[PDB]
């Protein structure tokens, strides 16, 4: 078996930084992991690959002719800890549906046997500002059974978490996609941990980890590395190791209870944010 | 004539706060303005209307039967300074295309004669994390001739500005949609104004105003008002008045020059962000 997980959240909240560091910690532990980038920004694997980014399936298919002219061994790339990496890509802005590349990529990976039994985890890093097209496909088509939402005390980040949860509820009659937890990627605000715990409880889930804001992230990323590789002794490396451990041990996967806008505002008012 | 403007930018960057305050300042000056909300969050008019939000055209059409059963006088609502307000709405998460309501709304407004000659400005407040579907329609279909992008020193906010600019370039052969400027909505970071000026120069535009981070915004919004209405003497009210004046006087509308990821990273490295 393998655990298929998707990391969702609003743009800029820390999906790719959190995913790549979490996965590096899992690889450091001895797990076999694949990351599938499902965000048009297409830099979801660069810290594993030590790279600028990664050429996308959409780009490589266009240069080869069709996606069938591609071979998996040409598309998947291995980096830190043997983690395997692939980017979906997507159409240029103003052209077609921004999520169309996700559908092409996941189908290609399935057909070509990328989901070999020896994998322990797959992580999809998915744009979450809209829940439609290819960005909804991991939920709609039962590709990621465990959804973890990166958020913060920012109202927009909490709204996004609630919106993603509404999408999970919409497809709960089929497949087995569930909300696994919230990950608070801190903005260094007071009581932020308490706020995200409260939100998770209202949704029916948990806050799986509170990730502190730490400048070591930027110093590692300037050098195209995870904190795990860049400075294994960093306090922030231990934070990502704690997040990885709790993801491994997590057994709570729920159909969430989306809340009203009044509930979100009350949370913010209460915790003095 | 009227000036048709659209405010784009990544989620949570300050589009709705900036738009409603800018428009309040324009109304305070004696201009006649309409705001069209083009973000599924659907709270782009609440500070003009003193409201929780506004019921959307998609919602009202469903309750009436068809969009043709709606009357403009039932849909448009007037608030502070006589500013007229309408919300597009959109499908629930996981269902259909998140931007579909924008197409329905703009077409309804055009057909029903909402664009009366006495209007001086129309502002569309548009989700910008993806540039596709109804979110691209104001650009693709020549609805907003002047695009202003709210951003900040945040890398993701600058990436979004570059992405929106790529969409403008894509449709420059038809219609007359142009980039009018960048608005820096500050994160209280050092040299942020210099950084956004540099980005604007690389794109071929200008930074039309630097909006400071000021807690008076939250105090006004808790009370469902713009800063302009809440505390007309606030320093931040004068900031929005300066932004409004410069939008009124702006004559630079360009086909932008999108930059490479290396250029963005160099900007960030240079200004020590
Ligand atoms: N815990 C953290 N501490 C410091 N910086 C962070 C942290 N998490 C993310 N960042 C920074 O935030 C920015 C956006 O993170 P990213 O993972 O790219 O967001 P997303 O993938 O959700 O768009 C990056 O520059 C990253 O270095
Ligand atoms: N200049 C500012 N100073 C302080 N808070 C701000 C400022 N601009 C925006 N905000 C706050 O940022 C949050 C997001 O702004 P909003 O306009 O809703 O973003 P968007 O419409 O782009 O999603 C709001 O809570 C708003 O009060
Ligand atoms: S939102 Fe992008 S195409 Fe439907
Ligand atoms: S991105 Fe939303 S439907 Fe195409
Ligand atoms: Mg990312
Ligand atoms: Mg808004």
Image (cartoon, coloured by chain):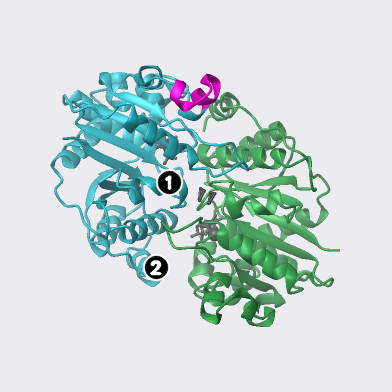
Chain colours: A cyan, B green
Q: Is mark 1 within 8 Å of ligand 4?
A: yes
Q: Which labelled disc corresponds to residue A13?
A: none
Spot occupied by residue B116 in the image (x, y as percentages of width and height):
80, 72
**First along the sequence among labels 1 and 2:** 1
Tell me if residue A215 can be seen.
Answer: no
- Cα distance, mark 1 to mark 2? 27 Å
Image quarter where the N terminus of chain B lies is bottom right
Would you name the residue on which mark 2 appears? A265
Spot occupied by residue B262 in the image (x, y as percentages of width and height):
57, 24
Residue A67 within the segment the image draws in magenta: yes
Q: Are marks 1 and 2 on the same chain?
A: yes
Q: Secondary structure at mark 1?
A: helix
Residue placed at 68% from the left, 55% from the top? Answer: B6
Q: Quadrant of residue B68?
A: bottom right
Tell me if residue A240 can be seen.
Answer: yes
Spot occupied by residue A141 in the image (x, y as percentages of width and height):
34, 47
Write down which quadrant ligand 5 falls in: top left
Magenta range is A59-69
Q: Quadrant of residue B120?
A: bottom right
């Amino acid at each position: 078996a393998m655990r298929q997980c998707a990391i969702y959240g609003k743009g800029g909240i820390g999906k790719s930084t959190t995913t790549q560091n979490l996965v590096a910690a899992l690889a450091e532990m001895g797990k076999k992991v694949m990351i599938v980038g499902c965000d048009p920004k297409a830099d979801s694997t660069r810290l594993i690959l030590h790279s600028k980014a990664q050429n996308t399936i959409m780009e490589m298919a266009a240069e080869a002719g069709t996606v069938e002219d591609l071979e998996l061994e040409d598309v998947l790339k291995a980096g830190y800890g043997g983690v395997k990496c692939v980017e979906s890509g997507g159409p240029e802005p103003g052209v077609g549906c921004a999520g169309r590349g996700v559908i092409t990529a996941i189908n290609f990976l399935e057909e070509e046997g990328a989901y070999e039994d020896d994998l322990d985890f797959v992580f999809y890093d998915v744009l979450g500002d809209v829940v439609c097209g290819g960005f909804a496909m991991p939920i709609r088509e039962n590709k990621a059974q465990e959804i973890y939402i990166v958020c913060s005390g920012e109202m927009m980040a909490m709204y996004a978490a609630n919106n993603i949860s509404k999408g999970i509820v919409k497809y709960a009659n089929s497949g087995s996609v569930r909300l696994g937890g919230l990950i608070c990627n801190s903005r260094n605000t007071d009581r932020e941990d308490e706020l995200i715990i409260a939100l998770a409880n209202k949704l029916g889930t948990q806050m799986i980890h509170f990730v502190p804001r730490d400048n070591v992230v930027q110093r590692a990323e300037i050098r195209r590395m995870t904190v795990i590789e860049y400075d294994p002794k960093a306090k922030q490396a231990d934070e990502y190791r704690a997040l990885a451990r709790k993801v491994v041990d997590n057994k709570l996967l729920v159909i969430p209870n989306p809340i009203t806008m009044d509930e979100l505002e009350e949370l913010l008012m209460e915790f003095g944010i």
